[PDB]
Image (cartoon, rainbow, N blue to C red):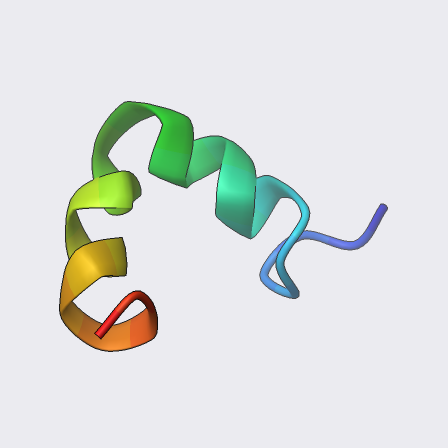
Amino acid sequence: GIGGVLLSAGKAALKGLAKVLAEKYAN
């Protein structure tokens, strides 16, 4: 585990960032 790599960077997506997901990443 690191943090802002994809791991807990992903854990944050669970909550909010799965929003930004469809925007940038899922884009």
